[PDB]
Length: 72
Image (cartoon, rainbow, N blue to C red; front, side):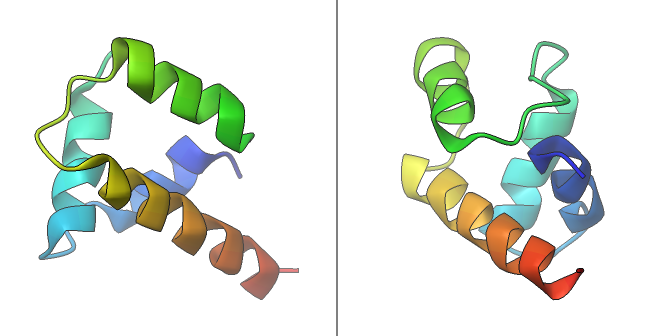
């Protein structure tokens, strides 16, 4: 599962992660198949147009990795 796919399961959550999840969803340009942190952070820095602090993305990616480890 890519970061984007994971984010998709986060949609609806009633906090900042859920809010960012929705913006990532609304971003027609977001990289949908990438999982590498640098690639993703590169995108958010240059293309990112989000209302939440960068730390929210970091936290979201952190959760992503825990989530993967929890599968497998």
